[PDB]
Amino acid sequence: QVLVPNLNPTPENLEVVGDGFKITSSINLVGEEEADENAVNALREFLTANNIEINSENDPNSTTLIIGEVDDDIPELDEALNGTTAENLKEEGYALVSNDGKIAIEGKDGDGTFYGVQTFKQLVKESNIPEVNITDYPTVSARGIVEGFYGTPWTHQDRLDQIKFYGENKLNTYIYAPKDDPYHREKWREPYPESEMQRMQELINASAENKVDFVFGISPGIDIRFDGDAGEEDFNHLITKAESLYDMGVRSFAIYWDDIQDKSAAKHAQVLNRFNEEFVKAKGDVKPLITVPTEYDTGAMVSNGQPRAYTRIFAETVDPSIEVMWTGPGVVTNEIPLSDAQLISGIYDRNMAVWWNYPVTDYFKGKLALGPMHGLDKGLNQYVDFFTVNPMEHAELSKISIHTAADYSWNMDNYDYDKAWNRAIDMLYGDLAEDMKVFANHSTRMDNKTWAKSGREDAPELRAKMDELWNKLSSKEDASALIEELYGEFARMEEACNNLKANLPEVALEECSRQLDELITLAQGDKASLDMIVAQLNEDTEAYESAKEIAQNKLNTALSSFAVISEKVAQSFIQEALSFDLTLI
Amino acid sequence: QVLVPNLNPTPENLEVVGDGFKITSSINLVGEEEADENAVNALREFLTANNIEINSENDPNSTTLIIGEVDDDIPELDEALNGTTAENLKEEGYALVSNDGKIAIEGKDGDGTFYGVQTFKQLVKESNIPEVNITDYPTVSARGIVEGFYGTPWTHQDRLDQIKFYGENKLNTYIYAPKDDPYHREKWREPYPESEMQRMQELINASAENKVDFVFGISPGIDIRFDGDAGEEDFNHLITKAESLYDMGVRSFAIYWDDIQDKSAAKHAQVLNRFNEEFVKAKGDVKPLITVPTEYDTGAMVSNGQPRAYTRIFAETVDPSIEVMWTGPGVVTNEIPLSDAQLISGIYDRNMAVWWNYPVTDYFKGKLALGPMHGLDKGLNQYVDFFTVNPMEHAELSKISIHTAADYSWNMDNYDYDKAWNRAIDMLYGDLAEDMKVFANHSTRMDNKTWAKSGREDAPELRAKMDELWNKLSSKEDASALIEELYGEFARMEEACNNLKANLPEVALEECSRQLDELITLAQGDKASLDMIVAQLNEDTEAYESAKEIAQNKLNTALSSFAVISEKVAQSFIQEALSFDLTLI
Ligand SMILES: CC(C)C(=O)N[C@H]1c2[nH]c(CCc3ccccc3)c[n+]2[C@H](CO)[C@@H](O)[C@@H]1O
Ligand SMILES: CC(C)C(=O)N[C@H]1c2[nH]c(CCc3ccccc3)c[n+]2[C@H](CO)[C@@H](O)[C@@H]1O
Ligand SMILES: [Cl-]
Ligand SMILES: [Cl-]
Ligand SMILES: [Cl-]
């Protein structure tokens, strides 16, 4: 009878109180004079998009929408809320009540009001809305993305689209830090050309319109000089560089020390402290300084329960108000258990920031990382106050994983990776969701075979059916039913990928066409591998020898291609099938 | 001056009691006419081959060999042993004392005297013998090989040479059960043709001369009938077949029920019991009957602590005298822990026989299994009294692993797999042992990528070095010295293999030429992999692309080839290097 639509992030408190109601083609709007401008703009936009007019004069027979903040002078807001408010209720928190023709939205601040509008937009389908009482606020207070990868940086239009996407999903933090922007790191002293400054401006305006904090990152560590007149000259270059962005509206800064040879911990921190003093504190409206030290994962930072020398000196030197990011137990790592966050938090005795290197693929570019947040302790917020993911150079397909990060960082305690992953693809993909899940299911696990591994395993259910096939065959048990089933699975992989090639919008298709072709090749090799097994069981030598040729040729195509998908599953199945001797008789 | 040479098996109690001495050009021999016939005949062969004559006549000044059993009354033996004796040792035990120009060999029985001679043969080098006090006896009472694999059965010459090899290493059991001998299984009812029988006579005679129990296996399970007249006809067929081999001197027999679809536990065990009664006991001089049940690995036999339906019925129907074989926790598995043997021995209420599926490679024929007995509990004799290995269709190279089985089963408590493996190769390959070690080190681990896995990991020390390389490179640490060390290892892999190709005797070379060429190919890819890494460090794109094309080609060659070696080490390393992105900035 509505119902409650898919929502992201999952609201903290949601109660269904009624049958639901249709929103009139024309509404009455109250409070839009005092409410958060940004919030109201996002409301107007949605209303316009959905062919909903705003009444110039009040109308009894119309759906009424009331909007404002807690301390705004708005009587009707108090009334339609009927008891529950956002009072109450941390920063970015809000209350939403839909009941019998009225919709009320109240934020603790303007951010909350904006976010209340985002939930509203998600609640309405076909002008119908469920009847609910919502109170909501984030688990973690900074949530977002660091564009911090190697490779082709996101285009200006990519970033503008990403920023709207963060706002819509309650993500409030975007860190500008592309390794391959020359003015970010390689030529960090050099000022941005005019045309690129105008683009930053648009990005900064876009961030503000969406209640996202734009963080200007800089990475001087390759060749910054520390002592004497050169240290003076270089420190001034940092100040100059930050000022140009500040003067455009930037109020958040990051200075980064990763991926460099120099491990002068005291000098790094001293730079951070001087910048913090002469810029951050001196400007007065600037958020805490953000940094990553040269040791940034637990393997690098810690030896036998104790901080290594670099980490030790850095921790003892960097001012307490500076946000320090770390990536977890490893740079690209399976999990962050609570004990790791506890370890690092105690070392720095401060709440930590997380730089999560997933879905980034810059270290294994042939594979797309399409899985949810996976391995992050649901209790991490005890030690972590700031959470960001490093995405792929592929902006559109990063939205799947980013979508889950939004849910993880806003409602951490109830986060369910499988449900969040499904919900992400449903919400992003529409009619194509079921097919996109088939494909993406095979492309969640990242593994470069050495130091870098993270993500949910690829297609775990299918992997379990494959194992059971081998179990039955080696036990000489009848596998006819399981074989018939696996034909069904392989045919479904291929059909799903074909539907995706024919119907994915180009923005999506351009990022994954090769991996799609790759999964089809694999599915075909998997099918032929079944043919090979079935021939061996039928003692049909010629059907063997013909199926095996196909299987091997598909595996060889898959191995020689740039695109990489389903290594431990669709790919490995062929290898397993070719290594299983059923000619033993 | 003079050290104890490599011995196999490791004697139970050995002590160096002096400096050693040289045996003269001719000796006094004493006890020949009373000591065991096969022991003396083996002794004479050795004396003839090492250009040592026997006095006519006796004295000077000439070294004195005295030989016999405890049951014999030879004074010189008693004087020469000086307190040491075989009197209190188990069957197959012996005493050897070499001191002051005397060598005394006393067996507990004729088997023990023979083994005494075998130890003597290993003790003498260039006429020099260490002065020692040995008492010795096997841990496990039945120690041998079952030729029980699928594929081309060993040739008749193969078998004769194996049987002598078993003698020399104190293995006492040979089970004749090749899956693809028609008359063993496919045509189990049918008599062997005459020329086959003559070959069987030779096998039987050779076994007797080398104290080896020749065990005749029959596998009637595919199509044997049990009920009514058909069941009579078929039972008599078993009798006819056994009689024919008994009539030539066979006194041990096996009836195998493995790898069939018929799970008729009562019928199987009834056939066993009927044969035990009408053949084994009726003859009086036939050793206990040996069997394998259709369920023969713990996974197939047991469901949480308890026997499955078939095993329950088998265990409780089969006569207590019958030796039952099982393979361990799985058909081809990592280990047999004491707890597994306890569990299975519990169900059958007796000491078990082991059929150990290593070094057999019938299920993964591209790889040679050249490693030691690995994963078998060193206390297994508590529940096991019968130990055999299923070897490769490649008889010559099977000797490395068999050699280690001889040590494990004879001296279980002191069994050290690395040392036994080293000794095997030292003792078997002589001048080529160091090169053979390099190559064989890469070919210990069996793994069909699904249900079958067993053996020591391939080249473990190189694997750790590889691991340490990636840990340093991903921490952006200086690895120049290790890089250099690994260039040395890959070069030495290629060198060893080249020498093996040029100098292996043909009978070994014909079994491993393809695998030699595989390891060379991979060493070359490994070397190209290092070059590829070094180029990326130097930001030399041309050298990188060039080394990369080579490393990829070498890999693809190895992957496409029938021969398989060093999957997780030499081969994996190339895959690891290719996925390590060092072009990031
Ligand atoms: C801010 C750091 C936590 C960090 O992750 N720095 C860089 C980083 N460093 C590393 C490990 C060291 C390394 C090895 C090879 C090439 C470049 C870096 C991995 N990463 C990320 C994933 O590839 C990459 O996106 C990121 O820009
Ligand atoms: C007597 C049994 C303990 C036994 O191991 N039987 C056969 C046996 N059965 C099995 C498992 C069943 C099987 C699976 C696939 C193909 C053939 C048999 C494995 N093996 C051995 C290793 O391949 C093979 O040498 C052996 O002859
Ligand atoms: Cl899990
Ligand atoms: Cl193809
Ligand atoms: Cl029958």
Image: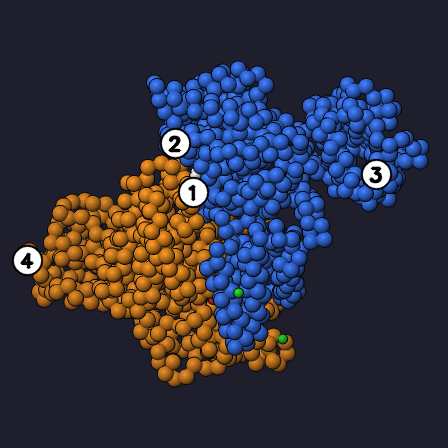
Chain colours: A blue, B orange
Q: CA distance from mark 2 to mark 4?
A: 87 Å
| Direction bottom: furthest residue | B194
Q: For the residue marked with disc 2, what is the amino acid?
A: Ile
The percent coordinates of residue A390 (x first, y second) are 54, 38
- The residues tagged by marks 3 and 1 sit, at their Cα atoms, a distance apart of 52 Å
Do circles 1 and 2 both sit on a common chain? Answer: no
Question: What amino acid does circle 1 point to?
Answer: Leu
Question: Is residue B285 or residue A494 the one in the foreground?
Answer: A494
Front tag of 3 and 4? 3
Q: Marks 3 and 4, how far apart in space?
A: 128 Å
Residue located beneath label 2 in the image: A222
Secondary structure under tag 4 reads loop
Q: Residue at x 58, y 44 (%)?
A: A395
- The answer to whether residue B503 is visible is yes
Callout 1: CB less than 8 Å from ligand 1: yes
Question: According to the image, label 4 marks what residue?
Answer: B60
Question: How many residues crowd mark 2 within 10 Å: few (<14), some (14–19), many (20+)?
Answer: some
